[PDB]
Amino acid sequence: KVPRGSHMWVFGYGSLIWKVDFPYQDKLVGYITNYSRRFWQGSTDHRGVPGKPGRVVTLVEDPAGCVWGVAYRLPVGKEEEVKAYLDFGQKGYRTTTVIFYPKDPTTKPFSVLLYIGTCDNPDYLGPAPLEDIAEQIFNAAGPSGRNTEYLFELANSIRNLVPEEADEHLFALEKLVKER
């Protein structure tokens, strides 16, 4: 099309795939490499509560990893302001820039903003057997709804975008909770 004077894309890997409250003027299905998506982050403000946390996704460095999701272009001339809105909502998350590979075989890979949760983050739980993650999810609910709803919306979304092979961790957990 016609060149724009500015560009900023943010990569969505969690709830951003099905729910965005910020404005965007394009979105593309694709993946990033060198990270894996893990249910190793506590939720005490959305999908659980203090004393009974939920498990939501967090990205971990994984050289052989990939994360399928959605990149969202921030509105041209409004990228910095919209970034700020994201940056001051991040209970914190660090930012980096990674190559995003569009699912489409017509659009070239490009640099996207990536929000990464820290080990320094107080809600971080860390790894746990998948049986124990699914139990937690089944039982957890927060101010934004059941932890189960989160997992099923993420699983349904990624399934609508790519085969299930695209994320074994997610689909083990999903089909896992489904057992209840």
Image (spheres, rainbow, N blue to C red):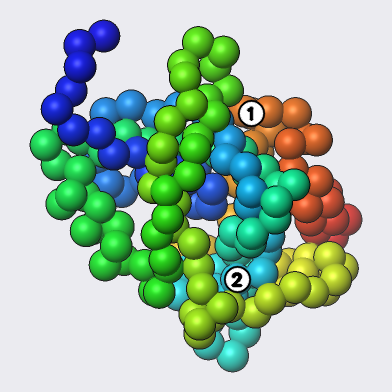
State the residue at coordinates (62%, 42%): 33
Give the CA separation, mark 2 to mark 1: 24 Å
Residue 55, image x, y percentages: 64, 69
Question: Is residue 71 among what the camera can see?
Answer: yes
Q: Mark 1 packing: few (<14 Cα in 10 Å), some, or many (20+)?
A: few
* Res 10 quadrant in image: top left
The quarter of the rendered structure image containing the N terminus is top left
Judged from this view, the residue extending furthest toward the front is 63
- On screen, residue 102 versus residue 170, left or right, reads left
User: Helix, strand or loop at disc 1?
Assistant: helix
Check disc 2: other Cα within 10 Å, few if <14, some if 14-19, many if 20+: many
Q: Quadrant of residue 110?
A: top left
Foreground residue, 54 or 138? 54
Q: Is residue 142 among the parts visible in the rendering?
A: no
Residue holding disc 1? 160
**In percent of the image, x 40 and y 74: which residue is there?**
92
Q: Position of residue 56 (x, y in %)?
A: 60, 64
Can you identify the residue that label 2 sits on? 41
Q: Position of residue 167 (x, y in %)?
A: 74, 43
